[PDB]
Image: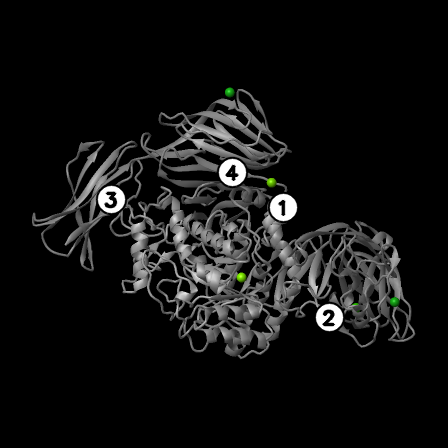
Amino acid sequence: DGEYHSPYGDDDLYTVQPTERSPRDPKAGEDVILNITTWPIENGQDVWVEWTKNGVAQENVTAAYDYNSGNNTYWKADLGKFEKGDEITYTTKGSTNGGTAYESGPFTFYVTDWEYVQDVTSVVDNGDSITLNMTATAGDFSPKLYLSFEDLDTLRMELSPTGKETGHAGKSGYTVEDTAEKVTVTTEDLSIEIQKSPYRMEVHQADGTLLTSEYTTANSLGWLTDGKNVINQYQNNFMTPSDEAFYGFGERYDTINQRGKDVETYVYNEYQDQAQTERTYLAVPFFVSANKYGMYVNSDFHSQFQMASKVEDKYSFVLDNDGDMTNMLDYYVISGKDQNDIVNNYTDITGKTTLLPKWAFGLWMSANEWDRESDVSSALSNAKANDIPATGFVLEQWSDEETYYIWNNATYTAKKNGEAFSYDDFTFNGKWTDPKGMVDSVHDAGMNIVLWQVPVLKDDGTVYEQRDNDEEYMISQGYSADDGTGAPYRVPASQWFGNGILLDFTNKDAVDWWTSQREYLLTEVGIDGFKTDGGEMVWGRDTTFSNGEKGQEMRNRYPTDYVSSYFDFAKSINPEAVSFSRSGTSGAQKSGIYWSGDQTSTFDSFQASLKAGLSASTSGVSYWAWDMAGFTGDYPTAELYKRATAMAAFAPIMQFHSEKSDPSPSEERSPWNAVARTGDETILPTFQKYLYTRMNLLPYIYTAAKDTADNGKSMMRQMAMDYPEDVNARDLDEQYMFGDDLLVAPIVQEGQTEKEVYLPEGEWVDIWNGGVHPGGETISYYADVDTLPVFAKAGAIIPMNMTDGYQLGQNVGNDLKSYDNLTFRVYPSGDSEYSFYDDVNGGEMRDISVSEDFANEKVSVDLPAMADETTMQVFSTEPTSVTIDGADVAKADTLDAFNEATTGYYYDTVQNLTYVKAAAKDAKQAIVLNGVNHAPYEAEFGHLTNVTTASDHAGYTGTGFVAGFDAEKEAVEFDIDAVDGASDYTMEVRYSAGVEDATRTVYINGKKQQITLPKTANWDTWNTVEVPVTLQAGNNQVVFDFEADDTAGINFDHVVIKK
Ligand SMILES: [Ca+2]
Ligand SMILES: [Cl-]
Ligand SMILES: [Cl-]
Ligand SMILES: [Mg+2]
Ligand SMILES: [Mg+2]
């Protein structure tokens, strides 16, 4: 028998327990209902409420029967409505036939209403902060809003509704113009305009361009209070035009543009249906707008961002508080040089990404079913047999599944009083007879290993000596959080690890103990980090932490305290250790890799993972991973597996994983098991191609990882992050930038082979074959299941680790200590510069510069001192000569001769790349390619009408030529760029015409001219004709037609644009 009521339940955002108060936090005019339970179900029960209003005893309120369920009766008591300032205290009671009474409480609530800023009554400029003294729309407070600058382009607002708290100092580099009606605050980057009556702020760039502004009708900034004991919420409201896009908010699975949605800053463990439920494990109260600003609400409390979800032209935030009247509202409006600089400024406030070792950027292998030494040995042998040079290895099913720091099957004498074990304390048996030796074998394969962990001490109600000993110690030492009554906090019973006790990561002594238990894994077993799973486990408003904070404030912070504690611990022992986690909030980026969690093997889930990575990127979480092709559900199709592999190889962290613990057949998402499960042997070479390409690009990828850590620029980025003004880029979620230079367009739709790719203005070159694609439109690219469209931007300098074959997709292995052939791929365009992070040679930054001067048929490369031989691969026509420091270097006729040479050059006619080899030297070297033009536009890559291609007459550039172009109605169209700006140019047409003179009609952006192509000696003889053309900015449509007045057959190799 009993009775129970608890007003907040578990404080869950999405559900209520059946014995809560509704509303949880009543405002003025809201009917308050109390839900109460009694048990068992029986006649003669009476339930009632004893209470006071402002200290005055009220008549008891009797509860009415609502419904029965299980062994319980549920009741509702109606307290009615209240006025702002009312203080209500109540106790719920139950008894049967006037017998024993059971009760809950007392519970108190303070009835609130909103008060807003009205006018600015005075301004005080203290030199490093500005105070705006204001009046309020209601109540008796004297609010103060403090303005300060975190930097000249980053504004901080701190509101004290009572005026009793003071804002923080910032930079002094600002000026103020204060008039009776308005105050304007100016820095070299911002112009902040503030109307005084009513108060309203507009944030502009220094040149006057509006970034964002408070809502038009003013009274935008407010707080929810009873006027005496409590401040429970804050809000501000802003004006937004119909086309404004909002990105970030942590890791989001539903959309990359949150306009139209209410976004909850609330961490949650949602399995498989994150997109549909709009939930996430990683929530951050920061967004970036394509209107060139970011907004960061500096609080760990839950907030709701209403992004034009209520009123078409308004966005708002509503920030919760625990009632403490001394907690100021603190938020930032962040500008910068560009969108990535906005993210950099955000990381100045919340923490920079910590650079991880290069091994983190190779392939990670994982499968939950790996639960014994023989599984590890077989995984290593399978990788070797299938030529998969991975660098990361994860074990999940490794422990006793009780303590989570002891190897499965190990025996030992249990320890009391929180004492830690050493390796020699264990007798290793069964599944793991020699963990240290197993780790050595993983290292010997060139891989690094991490072990799965959780932040909770498991308590399943079973007897297990060591766990029971640790639990008693942890509780009595005060190492858990407190439930609010002096008892240890436990995860709610219905949840993952329900009944488990959370380690209080705010308590340094608790953390030292917890990590001391795992110390031997790092010092003696030799592991390389931890997969710190979970963390979305703090419920309860009264849950109390050692830092004095409670559940509302700590729910979102807890996972990051957990993750960071482990990351820092592992690295203190092993400098090369890496964490792999899923949950966090602002600052998560400081502590390792984040993966997108638990998803199914479908194209819809693939689409959601990419949105999660792109939104996480904007939010400063750059080192992002996903379980390629899904970790659960029916085994992926060969198509999904292949499409996923390609995106995964071009994402920040590449990793496969599987959910099942003991399946038959195997559920491994490895390429060898994928071949086995689908019966499609072609999966292996396709996977190899993408893995080998990633390893060829590792020097570029790792430099990008460094740029994240140094400059806040995420590795994988949504298109609007690099092109905010481009209206076509605003909502794209099926392509992205990777590193500074590569536009990647994965196929994330089932059955798709015609991939649309939006190309921003500028020239884009297909990295696989040299196809040129002028930007400014959405192109169609035919991508079979093994193909991934990837393009390099104009001016790109891309370092690569190549074999003597010098093609993308050739295996260089997993040696992270040296390069095979360090190579720089260059797409010359004006003056470009690249800072390469040469980690192989001491982490020195090598500044490479390229100066394109095709008007004088030259491209110059300024190579700094290098420790290794270097090979340039420059996109161009074939040079007439190449000099290094003014001395000619020898032309090599074949790739073999090029490889044998110590210095020289070689021209790859298929790829239209000039290779230049320069020796290692302790000083800068000046390389100059002479007699070169922009690379040819191959006819075989053009848009063809009623003609085909072939490769049956030798001497063509590219892969062949257009053949059988010999009848009316046939045409070849090229999309061409002006090389050095809009101008007149000479278009060199290369063709063969073995039978007779030919003529064709050419249209340049619709302007007609006819050309004559003289007979060549035979079909094995090529000739060039020079045609004067006028080329403008952007894409030039160049059409070669065979009209009624044209004549004869030609083979058409390419066109070259020159001065
Ligand atoms: Ca050709
Ligand atoms: Cl004033
Ligand atoms: Cl020729
Ligand atoms: Mg800055
Ligand atoms: Mg080591």
For image coordinates 70% across by 66% down, the residue present is 820
First of labels 3, 2 by sequence position: 3
Q: Are marks 2 and 1 in contact (CB under 8 Å)?
A: no
Label 1 beta carbon less than 8 Å to ligand 4: no
For discs 4 and 3, the disc positioned in front in the rendered view: 4
The residue carrying mark 3 is 33
Q: Are marks 4 and 2 in contact (CB under 8 Å)?
A: no
Lateral position of residue 675 relative to residue 831, left or right: left
Residue 585 appears in view: yes
Label 4 beta carbon less than 8 Å to ligand 4: no
First of labels 1, 4 by sequence position: 4
The numbered mark at residue 942 is: none
Q: Could you tell me residue 304's position as x and y percent? A: 42, 44
The residue carrying mark 4 is 332
The amino acid pointed to by label 1 is Glu
First of labels 4, 3 by sequence position: 3
For discs 2 and 1, the disc positioned in front in the rendered view: 2
Q: Could you tell me residue 1000's position as x and y percent? A: 84, 65
849 and 839: which one is in front?
Answer: 839
The amino acid pointed to by label 4 is Tyr
The residue carrying mark 2 is 805
Q: Could you tell me residue 851's position as x and y percent? A: 79, 51
The amino acid pointed to by label 2 is Gly
For discs 4 and 2, the disc positioned in front in the rendered view: 2
Furthest residue toward front: 424
Q: Could you tell me residue 611's position as x and y percent? A: 52, 56
Q: Quadrant of the N terminus?
A: bottom left
CA separation in Å, label 3 and label 1: 51 Å
The amino acid pointed to by label 3 is Ile
The residue carrying mark 1 is 725
For image coordinates 55% across by 50% down, the residue present is 353
